[PDB]
DNA sequence: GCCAACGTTGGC
DNA sequence: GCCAACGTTGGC
């Protein structure tokens, strides 16, 4: 399920997906979805898209919070 | 050719 | 030793 991420612009959602198989089974990946539904796999990728819209320097990609 | 899913490693 | 970040690839 895609959760709302209030630290990002309206419409932004975070999803955490448990790996199901392989040696990394049990681990999890985090994704964000833009208001238009585009998928983001890393903080630099978000940064390049959001630019000056928000400062992501204090942003924890995994938890989706601003942690200073 | 695409991309979801897992593998992989450099930087800490 | 962990994990953020991105590379690889099997299945479609």
Image: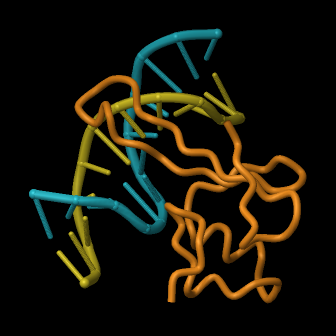
Chain colours: A orange, B yellow, C cyan
For image coordinates 28% across by 36% down, the residue present is: A24
Left or right, residue A53 beside residue B7: right
Position in image of residue B10 (x %, y %): 26, 73
Quick check: A45 above or below A11? Answer: below
Q: Position of residue A66 (x, y in %)?
A: 59, 79
- Residue B6 x %, y %: 35, 31
- Classify residue B4 as left or right of residue A8: left
**Total count of labels:** 0
Q: Nearer the viewer, residue A22 or A17?
A: A17
Work out whether A54 lies above or below A44.
below
Q: Quadrant of the N terminus of chain A?
A: top right
Closer-to-camera residue (A44/C7):
A44
For the point 70% across and 43% down, the residue is A2
Q: Residue at x 76, y 70 (%)?
A: A8
Lateral position of residue A63 relative to residue C10, left or right: right
Reply above or below: A20 against A31: above
Residue A23's quadrant in the figure? top left
Can you give x and y, in whole percent of width and height, for residue A44 in the image?
A: 58, 73
In the rendered image, the vertical position of residue A25 relative to residue C1, given as above or below: above
- Quarter residue A42 falls in: bottom right
């Amino acid at each position: 399920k895609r959760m709302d991420c209030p630290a990002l612009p309206p419409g932004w959602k975070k999803e955490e997906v448990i790996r199901k198989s392989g040696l990394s089974a049990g681990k999890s990946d985090v994704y964000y979805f833009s208001p238009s539904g585009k998928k983001f796999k890393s903080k630099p990728q978000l940064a390049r898209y959001l630019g000056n819209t928000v400062d992501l320097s204090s942003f924890d990609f995994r938890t989706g919070k601003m942690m200073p």
